Amino acid sequence: AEEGGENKSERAKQANALHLLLIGFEQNRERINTVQNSTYSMDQLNFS
Amino acid sequence: TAFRVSVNGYETSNENYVRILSEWGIPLVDQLIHDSGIESFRSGIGLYL
């Protein structure tokens, strides 16, 4: 709301990535481990 | 050698161990033991004695 847009500037860009990274972080937190770099697959993730 | 063993992160080490061996089988192990050189050691010392 303050920036009036996500990709309207470098400062807004950082909010855009942060907005989507935080949204991405919370949306797919169950597919992400703490330290070890999790390895998955279509069969392990149910992709057709 | 005559093998195309591919190691991937799709499976764990044990699962790859199961998959890799299931793909090729014992004949791969024959090369493994041959490369170890233990058999040559037995012949070497045995030949000397």
Image: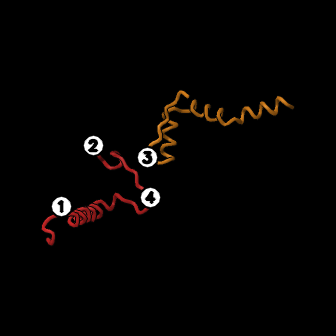
Q: Which residue is mark 3?
A: B9
Tell me residue B5's x, y (percent): 49, 35
User: Under tag 2, what secondary structure?
Assistant: loop
| Nearer to the camera, B32 or A7 | A7
Label 1, label 4: how far apart the Cα atoms are: 32 Å
| First of labels 2, 4 by sequence position | 4
Residue drawn at x 53%, y 27% as measured from the top left: B2
Q: Is residue B7 above or below residue A24?
A: above
Residue drawn at x 41%, y 63% as measured from the top left: A34
> Which amino acid, by three-letter code, is at mark 3?
Gly
Question: Residues at marks 3 and 4, common chain?
Answer: no
| Nearer to the camera, B17 or A25 | A25
Q: Are marks 3 and 4 in contact (CB under 8 Å)?
A: no
Q: Which mark is residue A36?
A: 4
Q: Is residue A41 above or below residue A35?
A: above
Residue drawn at x 52%, y 42% as measured from the top left: B17
Q: Which residue is mark 1?
A: A7
Q: Which residue is mark 2?
A: A48
User: Under tag 3, what secondary structure?
Assistant: loop
Left/right placement of residue B20 relative to residue A6 reads right
Please tell me whether mark 1 or mark 3 is closer to you in this view: 1
User: Under tag 1, what secondary structure?
Assistant: loop
